[PDB]
Length: 461
Ligand SMILES: COc1ccc(C)cc1NC(=O)Nn1cnnc1
Ligand SMILES: [Zn+2]
Ligand SMILES: [Zn+2]
Ligand SMILES: [Zn+2]
Image (tube, rainbow, N blue to C red; front, top):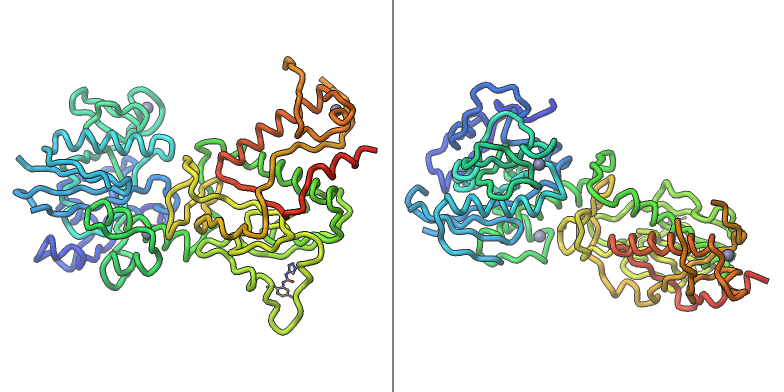
């Protein structure tokens, strides 16, 4: 059970309005044959055009919703819609394009998928709510065959060119006209009652139905993400490194240690309530503070209600008002005023952050985390945490050329003494790099209103 057997049954009830008379008994093998594709008994890495739900989840970065609506089926123009917002009209002679023949439409498809996916995935997975026309239109822009490599690099081939008779990956496909060996999954096969809009609207109010193919393509991919990442969550699935994952995670651990350590030194809290990851470790192991941990896995649907995080049933909760609360990526509706908070901003544009369900986003870095929509009102009791670098380490070099550092936010004994030493300047610039990496990845930092770095200077006496 590695791939989806071509002899698996495909429910054809969703297909019978575009294709009336379709057999109720249908296998993937017969469907693929009906679509105009010949697998010809080939054991070359492409056993089926269609993939399992499990394989689709492993390749979420490759998901592109796809819908086809009949504008007028051999003699009529089709509107091709993609979860990128693109609508192309193909004539058989929110971005809406005018009627053009397939030979030019297919060039645009390859360009669009290539620009969208080159930094996300080695493939495309068309996410469908299959009614018939999307499957029968594939033959006009898709070619299949054995698994191949790019003509310019070692990556797998995702495109084919009839002009040059060559294959390319998403990075080297300029001028290519066919999508080569794509994958697809039909959301309707999962067992739903009612149409696409009725199932999508149950979970999401951000995607409306403006009655174009791209709206359906968006809704289809949204509903798929809800089913695979919101209601059902899998933290055993690892995802490849496609960008700054390692640097971002390392920056996150540096910022956390810095901010929490300085909050403990500035306001000397006697107790810290660490609410979040059940596998969390003390980010400041040498701190005096009474460290108390509370387990809450990342919320993937709605933000946790703060009232429910403290709901102790028939017994008393701990006194959250005593000391400080640390919410490191533990997303709540409204933070207590005595908090240190790291909250991922779902609106961030990046190769790690994919569009999600109901305003939320699917953040993919080692694991997939569907995150609830960033909401500014969650931080009404707090303020934005300013950048600062703090260090009590000795002014000792141990060792990359140099320019003297002048900064009001380098909180060290040397800067108090009038001149930042080389070590603390090197460490300040590295910390500032890590800090900017974390902010630009989408993370935002918030703190209790009494926080003041001026209180850190007297820790050097
Ligand atoms: C669902 O939460 C609980 C369940 C049972 C019990 C006994 C306690 C809690 N909570 C709790 O004490 N949270 N806390 C965090 N910072 N101050 C208080
Ligand atoms: Zn290539
Ligand atoms: Zn939606
Ligand atoms: Zn120094």
